[PDB]
Amino acid sequence: TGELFFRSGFGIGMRKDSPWKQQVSLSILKSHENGFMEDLDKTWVRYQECDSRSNAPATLTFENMAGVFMLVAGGIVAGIFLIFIEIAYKRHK
Amino acid sequence: DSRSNAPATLTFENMAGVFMLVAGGIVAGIFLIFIEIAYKRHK
Amino acid sequence: WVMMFVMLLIVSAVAVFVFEYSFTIGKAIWLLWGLVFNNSVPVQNPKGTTSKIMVSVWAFFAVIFLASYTANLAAFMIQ
Amino acid sequence: LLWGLVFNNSVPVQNPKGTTSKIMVSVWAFFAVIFLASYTANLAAFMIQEEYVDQVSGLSDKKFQRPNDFSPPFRFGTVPNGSTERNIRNNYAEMHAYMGKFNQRGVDDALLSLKTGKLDAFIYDAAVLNYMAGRDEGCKLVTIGSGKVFASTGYGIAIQKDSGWKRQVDLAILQLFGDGEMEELEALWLTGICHNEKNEVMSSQLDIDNMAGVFYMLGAAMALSLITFICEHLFYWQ
Amino acid sequence: EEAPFVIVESVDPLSGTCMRNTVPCQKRIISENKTDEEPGYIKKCCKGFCIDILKKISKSVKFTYDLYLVTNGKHGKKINGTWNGMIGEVVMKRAYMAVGSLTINEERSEVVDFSVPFIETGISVMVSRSNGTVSPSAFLEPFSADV
Amino acid sequence: TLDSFMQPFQSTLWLLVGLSVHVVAVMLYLLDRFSTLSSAMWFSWGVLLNSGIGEGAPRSFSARILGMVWAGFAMIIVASYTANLAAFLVLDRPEERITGINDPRLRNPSDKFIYATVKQSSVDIYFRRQVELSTMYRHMEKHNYESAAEAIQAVRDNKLHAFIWDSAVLEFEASQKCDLVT
Amino acid sequence: ANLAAFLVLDRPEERITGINDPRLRNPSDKFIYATVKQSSVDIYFRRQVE
Amino acid sequence: IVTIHQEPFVYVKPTMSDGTCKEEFTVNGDPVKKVICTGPNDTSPGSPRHTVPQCCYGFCIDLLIKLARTMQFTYEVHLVADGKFGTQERVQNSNKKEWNGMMGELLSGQADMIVAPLTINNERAQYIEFSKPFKYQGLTILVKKEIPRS
Ligand SMILES: *[C@@H]1O[C@H](CO)[C@@H](O[C@@H]2O[C@H](CO)[C@@H](O)[C@H](O)[C@H]2NC(C)=O)[C@H](O)[C@H]1NC(C)=O
Ligand SMILES: c1ccc(C2(N3CCCCC3)CCCCC2)cc1
Ligand SMILES: *[C@@H]1O[C@H](CO)[C@@H](O)[C@H](O)[C@H]1NC(C)=O
């Protein structure tokens, strides 16, 4: 959450007054312009996302279906003995 | 008024959008009665 | 709502007019007041050709109207 | 009868004359109401919390690669002579060649051209564009995605070579980072007004583009009905 | 000058210089090419963000300064081994300091040097926000695909 | 609220749905030469309308499948209609509401906005004696008015974009005369 | 409407906005939060006065 | 080259029977480099002292390989002993103040480069020559989330 406040970037560091200074900086910066950095980005960091925000319109599933299909399944089997009595009820009058 | 959310009822301004067409349909069919009856006496 | 009801009266009068070309005004108004609300009560419809298109456009009014009512009503339970 | 009754009494039918049939159809109709109604809101709820997606993926997409092969191509240009085009003229030479057709001038003229439909895309520095969003009257302009960048560089202070002031200033700016007053400076200058989580505005009038699915379902139903007709007839006269 | 970093504004009509919270920068303009003018100079005042950070750094380490603008074009680029803009003005050992809106790249690091950056930036895409929404399969999305 | 018919559907849809009614009525008649024109057209144009009018039903097996899906077509559309209209009643624009001194909109005064205060009053003392707020005091002097009563009448029409004064005077003014707001 | 009302509302309770939430500046005993020892983050906090 | 352990940048895994570790492939199937990394084992080097070869693979070391192509040099990485980034403090109450942790080895004759998530700051920049940054970053907060209704 929130927003970043203390901002800076990681860096490669050497000892003071080394002959490798003036050449590494040119190379590392050159990588950004060519696009070599972005190729490595996709493969290692930004590849998997379970990030369906927060609103998340919920695709209602069969968990809801139990509360209604149980009722309808009752009627087909709770009427069978209601059938039995009424046809007999016709025979009784 | 207050409560800047402002949930407002609809009023007569929407009546014209519905009543005029259906009331217009009433007068649109008055002569249609005359037209169709003429067909019965035509053949 | 009174503007709705008076139009019920006028279209009932129009239906009476159409019949000149087993039907009663009570049955006609019952039909109309049924179709306005989800046509719940079964009713014997008239045999008039023009009256039938008239009640059809009335049903168009009924369906538009009702849907808006529902929608709008939500507007009021969440703000 | 029942398959039509599940959906607003739509089909006129003839009713069985029994009693247990009556109770069964009544309970099914009840199942009816809830199911239909529940479906209606849930759909309303879903369409309430939509998510707008811009009509582009990125600079690397084919939509910016072969403009000639699509609908009247995107009219997009950049202000010349900047560092932006030098990046373009070294990785997308053909795209740079196509660029010169419009060749915008300045910034404000480009913004106005975008507002009037003459232009439909723009490439320029990240820092300026992000600030330009929060100043316009209303909010009809937004960067792609979440403000993502495609070439991570930064501004700086350019000085003449080989002076100790290099060491002095370089060590000094980190002091300014240390105390966090640049947060105050940002809150005073580069902060923006609108664009609070991209709440979206409204869908309207639902033109043909979306109902294509239901129209295709109708056409498929007509086709399969005709196939069933021909199959039944050929099997029948035999 | 640029919109968010270096805003230019005319001086106060009464005193001669504008209000506080700024530094006076004087710019150069010359008359037509047929007849030119001898050091014709006009002063204005510049204020914004880079000006404030420069003032802070000057207060941090004691040294004075005086700001004067440039006229020969824009940011600058390499043509036939020559340079315009701020890079051109500093390559000839006549400026000694360039501030404002300078990007960073490969070539420029070979002529001038650079300090630690303080604002992340780069190349970005800006498009008009389409009026409408997205819903290719709206009518089927809710509820369930198995019930 | 716009117009009832036009606000939630584009004019293109009305033609396409309407013409299809005649279209979907056609092959129904053709499907009767497998093994009543006045009937078939009424059957379809009625069911979409959710009316209570109808005389007969199709008998051929070929049309039996087509009718079933045709009914489900109607329910989705009317459901689609009642859904978004609902979208209209819940969405509104923001922007104009400003948030006091902290708002960036009141620290770099462009030539589109004008402040306002009563001259030679308490408010002027608070600003000029501040330091970092001086950037707006310069824009402040060029438009200040003479007295309270004139200023309110000047903002009812588009002549002043904002006003600064006490709440105990403004609050009553907004509550009784309810064209404005704090 | 009732089922429509329930499916769209969440009543967001609270989240740590940043370094301005009074849930951190005036710490209670219901929150325990730490960093990595002898690290970059630790330097930033100690030098600050407020 | 001295590199501290980290989650997204330097993975560490034990080797296989033959001495190296088996080569695997990603969704693209392109080989991923497995340069030998000789770091200490266990959680802390306090009680034990064992040095065992492993192979470490990830993001930053690839930058080392790509950089080493232009500047022709060889390398042999090994992880730091203490396992902490490090800062400065006072010891024995004397006038001498020294660095401990990853920072120290660069200071006194045991390395010549650092490739790791080392943040730039005023104190460390006093005497070290940082090059240009290659990944702009920040620091934020994360907390547990709460399950919604059914
Ligand atoms: C971008 O740079 C080019 C340099 O080629 C500028 O073109 C010159 O503009 C000046 C200004 O009027 C003219 O006097 C020159 O004759 C132009 N030279 C050429 C070769 O066209 C161009 O103006 C610059 N773009 C902008 C917006 O200033
Ligand atoms: C009873 C009341 C209302 C309906 C609706 N139904 C939608 C399509 C058009 C027929 C009515 C669905 C529920 C929301 C109101 C509209 C069905 C049954
Ligand atoms: C560029 O330089 C070359 C030689 O250095 C010269 O002949 C040519 O005229 C120059 N052209 C421009 C446009 O500066």
Image (cartoon, rainbow, N blue to C red):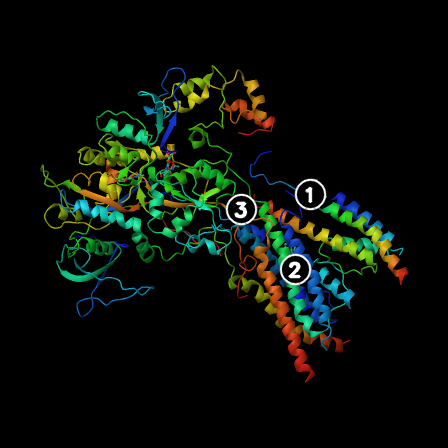
Q: Chain of mark 2?
A: F
Would you name the residue on which mark 2 appears? F74
Q: CA distance from mark 3 to mark 2?
A: 28 Å
Ligand 2, by image quadrant, is: bottom right
Residue of label 3: E131
Crowd band around label 2 with a 10 angstrom C-alpha radius: few (<14), some (14–19), many (20+): some
Do callouts 3 and 2 mark residues in contact (Cβ within 8 Å)?
A: no
Q: Nearer the viewer, residue C37 or G6?
A: C37
User: What SS does tag 1 mark?
Assistant: helix
- Across and down, in percent, residue D57 comes to 43, 53
Q: Position of residue D113 (x, y in %)?
A: 49, 40
Where in the figure is residue D110, as x and y percent of width and height? 45, 39
Disc 3 marks which amino acid? Answer: Asn
The quarter holding residue C24 reads bottom right
Indicate whether F80 appears above or below F141.
Answer: below
Query: If the image is split into quadrants, where does the N terminus of chain F sit?
Result: top right
Give left or right: position of H84 versus D100.
left
Q: Are marks 3 and 2 on the same chain?
A: no
Chain of residue at mark 1:
B
Placement of D64 over or under D229, stated as above or below: above
**Distance Cα–Cα, label 1 vs label 3:** 25 Å
Judge the density around disc 1: few (<14), some (14-19), many (≥20) Cα neighbours within 10 Å.
some
Identify whether H138 is placed above or below A62.
above
Q: Secondary structure at mark 3?
A: loop
Residue F103 visible? The answer is no
* Residues tagged 1 and 2 counted as in contact (Cβ below 8 A): no
Which residue is located at x 14 percent, y 47 percent?
H106
Q: Chain of mark 3?
A: E
Residue H8 x %, y %: 28, 54
Q: CA distance from mark 1 to mark 2?
A: 25 Å
To which residue does mark 1 refer? B14
In depth, the one of E122 and F127 nearer the eye is E122
